[PDB]
Amino acid sequence: VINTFDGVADYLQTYHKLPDNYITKSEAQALGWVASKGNLADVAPGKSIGGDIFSNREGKLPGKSGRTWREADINYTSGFRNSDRILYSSDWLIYKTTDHYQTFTKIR
């Protein structure tokens, strides 16, 4: 239902949580999600992967003590996951990537 960059971005800054169509990878695995099969839409119709913590290993997103980053899939409808993610901090900084976490730019 809400899975666009702008849509999810505004939902997060206002309501401080993901829309209802998101499930973490753990949740999805528990419903029978097998990444190598690209089946998420069969076991969880209308859902997207989102809410997992993003480690920011490469220190690309701005870091701060106490700030945790999470991710969510954008523009997903079916099949294997795409390369689009929204990155959101606990202080509601919003970044996007369209290249599998290689490049980030600010959107809120």
Image (cartoon, helix red, strand yellow):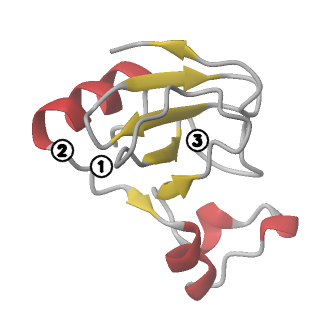
Q: Is 17 left or right of 25, judged from the image as shown? A: left
Q: Nearer the viewer, mark 1 or mark 3?
A: 1
The residue depicted at 65 percent of the width and 26 percent of the height is 60
Q: Is 62 left or right of 100, judged from the image as shown? A: left
Residue 102 found in image quarter: top right
Under mark 3, the amino acid is: Tyr
Q: Tell me, yes or no, whether the two marked residues, 3 and 2, touch with CB atoms within 8 Å.
A: no
The residue depicted at 51 percent of the width and 56 percent of the height is 53
Q: Which residue is mark 2?
A: 16
Q: Which residue is mark 3?
A: 76
Going from N to C along the chain, the mark reached first, 3 or 2, is: 2
Compared to residue 16, the image places residue 25 above or below, namely below
**Helix, strand or loop for disc 2:** loop
The residue depicted at 34 percent of the width and 49 percent of the height is 66
Compared to residue 92, the image places residue 70 above or below, namely below
Residue furthest right as drawn: 36
Residue 29 found in image quarter: bottom right
Q: Residues within 10 Å of mark 2 (few under 14, many from 20)?
A: few
| Mark drawn on residue 18 | 1
Front residue of 80/71: it is: 71
Q: How far across and down, in percent of the image, does residue 4 sit?
A: 43, 27
One can see residue 48 in this view: no
Q: Is 17 left or right of 41, judged from the image as shown? A: left
Alpha carbons under labels 1 and 2: distance apart: 7 Å
Q: Tell me, yes or no, whether the two marked residues, 1 and 3, touch with CB atoms within 8 Å.
A: no
